Image: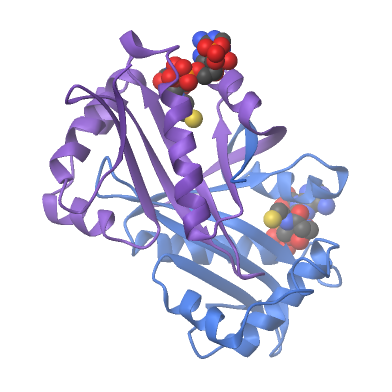
Chain colours: A purple, B blue
Amino acid sequence: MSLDVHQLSPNEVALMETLLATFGEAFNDMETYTGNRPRGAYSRRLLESDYFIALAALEYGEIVGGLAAYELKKFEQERSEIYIYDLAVAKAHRRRGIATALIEKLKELGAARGAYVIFVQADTAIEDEPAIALYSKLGVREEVLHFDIPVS
Amino acid sequence: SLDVHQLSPNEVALMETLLATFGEAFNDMETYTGNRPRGAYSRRLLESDYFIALAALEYGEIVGGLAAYELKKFEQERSEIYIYDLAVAKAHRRRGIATALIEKLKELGAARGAYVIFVQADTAIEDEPAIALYSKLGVREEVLHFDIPVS
Ligand SMILES: CC(C)(COP(=O)(O)OP(=O)(O)OC[C@H]1O[C@@H](n2cnc3c(N)ncnc32)[C@H](O)[C@@H]1OP(=O)(O)O)[C@@H](O)C(=O)NCCC(=O)NCCS
Ligand SMILES: CC(C)(COP(=O)(O)OP(=O)(O)OC[C@H]1O[C@@H](n2cnc3c(N)ncnc32)[C@H](O)[C@@H]1OP(=O)(O)O)[C@@H](O)C(=O)NCCC(=O)NCCS
């Protein structure tokens, strides 16, 4: 395997755009991830922010997977946690340890940031158990309730 | 009536009071207050533009509180507000306070381009008021939560 797990820099908005296409195909929601892409300026400032983390997995120059996460600096104590928002690997490239490699990279990035934990919500439907099997091996599962409150 | 407003960088002595309010709603007056950050640290956090701290007052004192994070999305120029903790003092429970905190967050989320506010709710019997409050302002979905150690 020639896998390269790479943290996107502010100098790599172009890579972020391709990663969005990887997310779209993997989530079967191309319209959401590529239908109204941000401007380079917006994407750039996000990449040079203190809390946003974008990882890309590459094979011979091709993006085959990636991860988007947010570092949450806490208020009750001097500590931080990393929230994995999106994580995806291209279909032809799955069951090969790419997602594991991405999370392993996020761990060593987290330890360098002083974060004490990484957490991620797993959807529960039929499409999910590959991710659930992935998350169950790395962390501790707990069943919670999620609510989407609308904003006008 | 009620007074819900956002905390400011030079309201750290009030944030630290809100930290205590969390400690009694949650019954863990040691995680939220047994190891509080430096005075220096907490203003840095309040001066940040993605962290949102809300305190509900009635008569010049804390009854409710909210701590949230604005998540600027990468796929589109939009934002999502993640409520991390929402708490109301027990003495003043069931008076529409938690509702007023979320309504305030809606108005500020709109001024940030936020299209949704999401919040997690566990399942323990003590948390049925939260689940009830949340189930009427948003549609529920049952998900799995995973805590992965950085170790
Ligand atoms: C979930 C996903 C990222 C996993 O990618 P991946 O690179 O294939 O995962 P890995 O190869 O590292 O697999 C790691 C372990 O997780 C388990 N696992 C992964 N996929 C599995 C599957 N379909 N079925 C059962 N177990 C699975 C296995 O234990 C695997 O280890 P193993 O091959 O040694 O048995 C990929 O399936 C995907 O992109 N799905 C679509 C989007 C999605 O669900 N994202 C999650 C958002 S949180
Ligand atoms: C959940 C909590 C914040 C609600 O606070 P609140 O100010 O009392 O709630 P509100 O007054 O605004 O209630 C609004 C609606 O929510 C529902 N609700 C609130 N509490 C309820 C309860 N014990 N039982 C049933 N429904 C309840 C009702 O529909 C209520 O409207 P109503 O009184 O007119 O019938 C509060 O109970 C609390 O702090 N609990 C402890 C901590 C917690 O669970 N936090 C959430 C996770 S961070």
- Relative horizontal placement of residue B32, taking residue B107 as reference (left or right): right
In this view of the protein, which residue sits in the foreground, A95 or B112? A95
Residue at point 20%, 51% (across, down): A43
Let me know if residue B90 appears in the view. Answer: yes
Q: Position of residue B62 (x, y in %)?
A: 71, 80
Q: Quadrant of residue B42?
A: bottom right
> Residue lying furthest front in this view?
A1
In this view of the protein, which residue sits in the foreground, B36 or A32? B36
Residue at point 31%, 61% (across, down): A49
Q: Position of residue A10 (x, y in %)?
A: 20, 54
Q: Position of residue A1 (x, y in %)?
A: 33, 16
Residue at point 69%, 90% (across, down): B60
Q: Quadrant of residue A146?
A: top right
- Label count reads 0
Relative vertical location of residue B124 with respect to residue B63 in this rendering, above or below: above
Let me know if residue A128 appears in the view. Answer: no
Residue at point 31%, 23% (across, down): A29
- Relative horizontal placement of residue A89, taking residue B98 as reference (left or right): left
Q: Position of residue B95 (x, y in %)?
A: 75, 66
Q: Quadrant of residue B70?
A: bottom left
Relative vertical location of residue A21 with respect to residue A107 in this rendering, above or below: above
